[PDB]
Length: 262
Length: 285
Image (cartoon, rainbow over all chains, first blue to last red; front, side, top):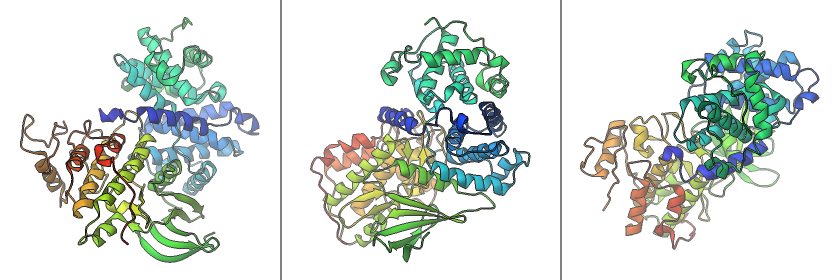
């Protein structure tokens, strides 16, 4: 029906693929960041996952926050002691943008264990807007995914939950996901889940939509297969903890395929 | 900071903020400045402002009001809009006795539909289309404004905020508490607004939710299969309305179809027979 916006689903997809290029963080901004590291960013993003889970925020919100963070850190030197304050500020911004009932500012100050005051959280908010110049409507993985989900035949909660799961795993690891577009990552995660749960593969319907072939999607699909395989051994574990729950059908408990047969 | 803007008069308040009319002292450019008070010890920058600013930066179309600049201070935020002469409501009221020429109604509708089709093409719901949020200039243009209840949507759409659209302009799916709603809701509004340009009275002026729905249930007709239409399962009913040519009446009832999935899209409406002859008259101000 109109909930699938028949007349506008393609126009929207065009625009989001253009905007995704425009909203893109600088690959390896971390090398230019004297004091913070990729490992540090992994601790942050993982913490954001927990925060979304505690407050029951949308998954869209989580992806927005991460975009907000990487773009900000793309242009603003940040000392480690201030890393969490950037991320708090972003979660707040993403919440305000995306949620019907975002948590209060006080709740964003509670989750920092009073590392920061309410006025630091708010001053960072204005700074973040200034640096991003209010460009907050950033396309995400989840946003492509949900469209890709429309081409299923039939639908599979497991694949859905499992495609979601894999997309999110990407957020944690700047290397190597800063070098893929949200659209590409989402294609890769959709294949990889579909395969695992059904044995099926990137649909032709979606080859016609995206212009992406399993050939185009292989550099990514390999990095994410590896990510999926070494996931139980990653230092960061909130995503897996999250997708063990039954809301997600315990897809973190399913076993990665061993070979993708490419 | 705002030393180059010189204030002229107040021109009202909308979803949020006070809007004044101003002149750039250096270029002579007349503008409108929405002034948004920030709560710098409390909630910081309002969610409504974050949405309007961001969404209105994406949206560059001649039938959508132009954000020009955004001036930050530590305690204030000022949105600099292009200035338009007045709103559809005020024009409709000045036009209460004379009427609005049927050519202009087409023009205004057409522009509104181009405008809104542009929104929908770009992942945005306006969600508060009402004559007071539509601005006209002296040369026959009309533009969507007040994007404070706007929202970037995903595909398919999720449950969004229930508290949306002024009652009169609110589509039935929202009234009935439907888990989902979509681009349908904005069309419904333009459908209500189409009618209001013709007659200059609002089409569904309810005092309450209950009254708002009964005015639609009536236009629908008498029962066929689904007996009480006050059900989240949108039954299939399109209204009847027997100075609007046969085409006009069709377009309207397509824009006001009770089932959201069958309601015309903005894109579709743009190609309707109604607009074959459509031109661009100037208004009588």
